[PDB]
Structure formats: structure tokens, C-alpha cells
Length: 343
Length: 167
Length: 125
Image 1 (cartoon, each protein chain N blue to C red):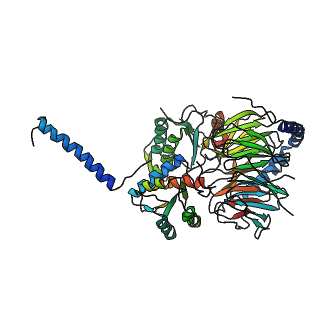
Image 2: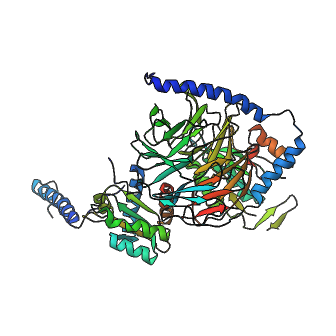
Image 3: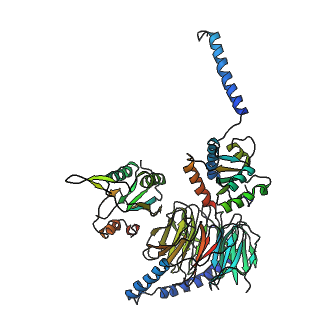
């Protein structure tokens, strides 16, 4: 084990993060609340919402995209447009109606990892070629340094920084503006299949193919708490909006949910058969939504973690899914090649 | 992993195999030697399964589940009203899973014995989750009975397993 | 070493061993068709369990129609690195760039086939 020196310029950023990060927590606590209690509303209201979510939803339409399965779909912060990535292609679609779409582009890359929106005109996409592309969506630059395929990419909650996580045991922290390598990080011993950023913008948790969920403090660059629970590769790492809980998924058909703040260890939802691809929490406001190759799609409480409901409209396996910010949409990319809007 | 080999690598092998043998026998006649013609599982984590059924009444089913659990070093438990859990190395579970689903017939009919005598009896099984856990607090595999749905939870409650039951 | 990115179904060294074992067993059980041509037929006919191709093919394009046929027919396809290696598993002294494990009635190989299918479906993301 070594401490590596260097990169003062990045050092500057850590300060920025600290100022930004530190100020965020008080607001998060205010959002959390507690004082009102009045349990009846919650149990009636929260329960009612969960029941509705897991009890009515259905297909609206299917749609098509390409002839390769669809590897990533993402909704914009206004939830009006979807981006769909094929093994080799993507196009941007209109949330409500879908159908015709706006317009397609065949990017220079052949097999698409993940696609993400800037929180505030831009997207970002990672793929097989080891090159991340900053897109301007009209009514920007390429990122270099990665040898292998890049599985996941995310925008810091802040807004300034992009972090990339690929296959060669390197998750790389990147700036949007300058397109520079702010941090080259090591520490897993095989592939690293996801990187997640947690809502105060303090911490990133890395899932890997070595079944070790490994937390990381961006500001000190210190490996913090290693999580062991998954006896197969950990595909998705989904952070929670509250910011004190994380959730993971894996080849083993399990979802672990670890809360560092409450010292709650891990509560395992036994979710799915046949893998898990992408777990998603509900952004605004509790619910979990996940996708495996079982063809079903699930709905979970964040309090009991009892499975509530499941929905089957896919004929094939599901690579990835994203859910409406209000929570009136659910968009799931079918393994076969459609994009299915869930009510 | 397996290699095959062609027709001509059979001949050459068959002939060079035969030749050595017959010539070795030939000298033996010249020389005058011969008259002239443990429970398995993984320590670091723990694979697990969970199963859920309508009836366990048949004893032949009640017995197998006690044996194989002790036979394969599966930790775990079982419960019912008036679910099944198993944990071990991943090889163990797969055997047991095969048993519960494909071998054993839960829909089959059996004639049970009561305190008075024998009577006929005329249920389904399906898996819920398989997965991975930080530690398996189950010490041994302990079949039991609960009257309610609550102490049933408190049973699992001891193991922080309340959630494994699904209504 | 690097393989053409386009050999999208790629098996690591472990899956590679299992695949080639199962291919070798299928050659023995007679559920094996060998050659891009005959593999194409099994797909059009609807009698294919799964498809295995060599990322070694000099004309990479000479077998690229297979994943397309496959996607349509919903048949798993995978790549291995070596066409000489595939050859050997097909009983052949010559390199074999594609091959098909075909459906067979009451196959002893069923469980193993099902297992291989699942592994390959996992790699498809």
C-alpha cells in the first residue's frame, strides 16, 4: 500500500467539493424532518401511494429502436425525453407518446454502456470503445484515458464533475469543462461495473465484478468501508435520495441495502431470479425499482423492503429501466428491442 | 475441456501402441520368459435460498428435509403455521433446490397415521429468492412449528430474518 | 490480447472451456452442425440450441450474419477466440469459424445445454 502524491489542480477541486458537500447535509436533514409525526397520514398516504404504484400499472405502447438489444435508457430532468442506447445505437424519444421520436444519430462507438443527463442541454454516454462523449442536445468533447469498455458513467450531484468507471480497475473522476483526469483510482482486482454518486455529493460507491462493494471518499481519496455480501458480480449500485442508504444488485439475484449512518448493516431483498441489471430509487420524495433477466420488473418499499408488486409486459430480458421523476412514468428497455412505457 | 483427434491420428496411435506390445512379447519367447506359443458452502459470504408452500403434512416430506439438511451441512431453518430457509456453499444449495422442486412431489397424495389409526390425505411449492448475505446467524437447521403468524416472525426475529416471510 | 470489438459475443477462459467441452460432447451425441453454412441452415430451420463462433475468422464479416439471424430467432450466440480450437472440438483437423448445437429429442445433454444457454444470455447486455 502507498500514498501517491501529485495533481494539485485536482486538489483545488476537493476543496470545492468540501465547501459544496458540507453545506448540503443540513438541507438533507431538514428534508428528513421527524417532528410532525402524525403517523396516520403516512401509513394511509405512503401506503396508498405504494399500493397504487405496485397495483395498477400497465403498458402504454411498445416502440422500436434497433436490431440489437437496448443497453441504456435515461430520462431528462424534465422527464420529457428519453435517450435509448443500442448495443451500437441511440435516439431521443418523447416521454409521453414516444413513437416517432425526435432524431437519431449513429455514434462513432459500437456498444453503449450508459447514458446520463446533466442535472441542470447535455448528455454523456460511455461505451465499448473506452471513449466518453459529451453531447450537446440542441433544442462537445471526447474523453480519453480508458483502455477497456466503460460500463457506467455519472454526473456528480453538484454539476461540475463527471466520474467514469470502466473495466480495468480504474474508476476515473473527470471535469465537464476542461475534460481532464481529476482522479485515477484503483483498488478492485477485476472489472468495475458501476459507480454511483450520493446525493450530497460526498461519496461514491463502486460495485465490481469481484463481488466487493467499496465505498470511497472523494475528498480524502480514502477507501472507507468495504461491503461484502455479493457472491457474484455487482452490476448496479443505486444510491438513495436520502443519502444515508445505498442499494446494490448483482449476478446473484439479490439486492443489498446498506445504511452507513444508521449502522443498519445490510437488509437483503430477495429480488428476481436470473440476475439484476439496474436498480432505481424514486428521485422525488421510498420505492425501489429493479430489472433482471427474469422479464419481470419490481416495486419495493424502502422501509420494510417487502416486495409489493410486479409487472410483466416484456417478452424478453430487460437490460435497463428508468422511472419518472414525479413517478407517473416507468420506462423500461426490453431485452428484445422495444422501449416499453409503463403507464 | 476436450481434444479430439482425427482418423490418421487414430491409426498411428493404434499401430504404434500395438507394435510395442507384440515385439515386447516376441523377446519374451526368445528370452524364454514365456512358454513359446464437511458440509460444504463458503466461509466469506453465504449463498442462500428460500421456499414457500401450502402444506407440509406428509411425513415422508418432513423426513427428507431433516436428512438432507444434516447430510449436506446446510445451515438454516424451517417453519409453518400450526416457509423453508437454507444456507451453505453454493454447491450444497443446488442439490437441495433440485430436491425440493424436481425430485419431491408435493402434489402427491399420502395416507397419514394419526393417534387412532391411518387416514387418507389429498399444495404447491415455488422458490422466492436466492442470494447473498453478510453472515448466516442460523447455527443449525431447526424445524419447528408456530401457531400464529407472529411468533413465527419472532422466531425469525431472533435471527433478524423477519422479512424472509411473504404473505 | 485484443479481439475485434465486433466479436461481441466473447467468452472468457472459463466459459471457453465449458463451451468447447459441450461442443465436443455434442459432436459425440450427434447434435452438432459445423460450418458457417450449416449453422445458418439450423437457424433458418429453427433447430438451433445456441451458436458458437471463432473471433479468429479472417473475414470477420463472413460470420457476422449469424448474430443477426440469432437475434431474430431468439437464439444465444457466443464467441471464442480460436477457430483452430473450435475445429478440434468439432472433431475436425481444420479450423471451424462457426458451429451450431442443434435441438435433439430427449437429449441427455439437455441440462448442460440449458446451463450454457443461461451463461450466454448473461453476457448479452
